[PDB]
Amino acid sequence: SLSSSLKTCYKYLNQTSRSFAAVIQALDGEMRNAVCIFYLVLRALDTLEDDMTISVEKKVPLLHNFHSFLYQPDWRFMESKEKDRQVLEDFPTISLEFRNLAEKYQTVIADICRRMGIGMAEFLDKHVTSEQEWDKYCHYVAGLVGIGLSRLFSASEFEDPLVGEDTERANSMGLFLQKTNIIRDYLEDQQGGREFWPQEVWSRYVKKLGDFAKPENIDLAVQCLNELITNALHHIPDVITYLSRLRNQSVFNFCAIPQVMAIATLAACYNNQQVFKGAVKIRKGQAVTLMMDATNMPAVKAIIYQYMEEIYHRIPDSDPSSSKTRQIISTIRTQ
Ligand code: NI
């Protein structure tokens, strides 16, 4: 039932999303192709942004005008040295399918690309300073994905207008995933010369973000870790509100699975020295269980509440964020 070009698009989706691909492919009806194409367009944009072999002077024009390449049938980019470069080399195939989408989906995807390109370009030289700047960066690379998705769901009418309307809750969905990834990936990012932890926070502990990798600094590193985890937890009430408003089963699964994965991850990272020694992962069986069970509101709430309990009873009295961590958890639990 797929055209030659759509066949190729799903192949790329599987190459670049692994799974998530199966969850996307389970989306009902018109949502499936819309989300598949949105994901590929975002992957192409992110592939440009990530590629350190592309100079800033070359990269900014590509970021600024990426949204316009969607309407340029022959546009491709042949000089990338990144893992997912096939989506850039074969962009014509993706944009062809994009232009085959209903106009209501095109409008959303183009708007999000435009906005993300501008934001990504703003952050190419600079690192993240304040907590407000952390939220801004996360909005650009992840919050806008949540906003775009929510707008696609409402436009398809498989979800209520409210989903696309409430940009704040949609933004939180994205910020929660992105902050979680940033926290978990401290060491991987360090070894790759990337710095995403906000300076207003870490500079309360060490003189350079890299100092957290030093074993004499483990206590300070964990305090900072716990502070950032506490920050991320503030998004959980919005995540619960967002999930609670979904009436489509395939949408609910698509939305809930990454969020329950993120919470399991934050729970694993909390007060955990191993964050600064390797990549803390969810144990493989457990990850598949959470995926398999993340299917209705009572079940997801029960999961989040259990993980919040595991954090709560691990909070060291001596942690400088201990009071705040307890308070957000009590807030999450009583929703
Ligand atoms: Ni420009």
Image: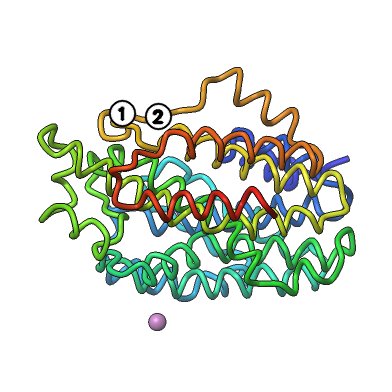
Question: At x 70% / y 50%, what residue is drawn?
Answer: 36
Residue at disc 2, secondary structure = loop
- Give the amino acid at mark 1: Gln
> Crowdedness of circle 2 by 10 Å Cα count: few (<14), some, many (20+)?
some
Q: Which residue is disc 1 drawn over?
A: 274
Rendered location of residue 270, percent (x, y): 40, 38
Is 267 positioned to the left or the right of 157 in the image?
A: left
Furthest-front residue in this view = 317
Rendered location of residue 118, percent (x, y): 45, 75
Q: Are marks 1 and 2 in contact (CB under 8 Å)?
A: yes
Which labelled disc corresponds to residue 280? Answer: 2
Give the quarter of the image for residue 3: top right
Rendered location of residue 132, percent (x, y): 39, 72
Q: Closest to the observer: 25 or 265?
A: 265
> Crowdedness of circle 1 by 10 Å Cα count: few (<14), some, many (20+)?
some
Give the quarter of the image for residue 212: top left
Give the quarter of the image for residue 7: top right
Which labelled disc corresponds to residue 44? Answer: none
Question: At x 55% / y 20%, what residue is drawn?
Answer: 284
- Mark 1 and mark 2 lie on one chain; the one further toward the N terminus is 1
